[PDB]
Image 1 (tube, rainbow, N blue to C red):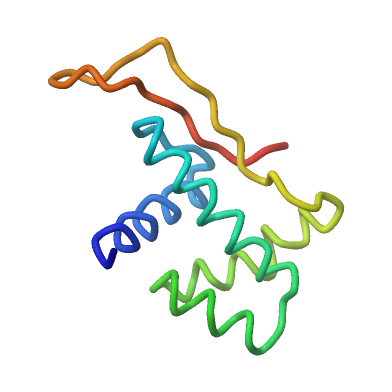
Image 2 (image 1 turned 90 degrees about the horizontal axis):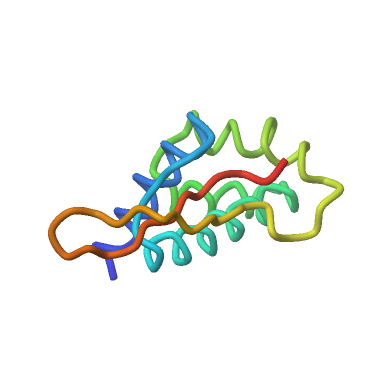
Length: 105
């Protein structure tokens, strides 16, 4: 719950900064949904959207980036802003299969 959102926020930060992230397949799916959700509000780009995005992402510089940088770039697409690609690689320990998450473009 609060543990998940903390993760999402951490993952989304790195994703918007470097452009890609790698995690487990499940965590990758959950993340893609969270980010698509944030970009949607950024595209709606209003007083209330900016409020909800910040409450979700506890980082101003990023919320700022989303609205005036990432959002404009996806004004043509209407969803599926994030791409998830399953790897042939599995993490060490449990062997859970990995997946690479990145912004479509």
